[PDB]
Length: 27
Image (tube, rainbow, N blue to C red):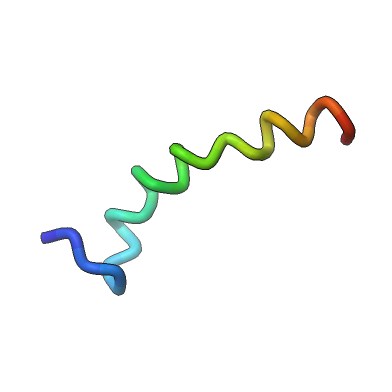
C-alpha cells in the first residue's frame, strides 16, 4: 500500500518537505 517504489505515496511525503518555503527567504 505504501512502498518506496510507489511514488504515488511519496507525494504525501513531498508535501512534508516545505523547503521551497525556506528557500523563499534566500531565493
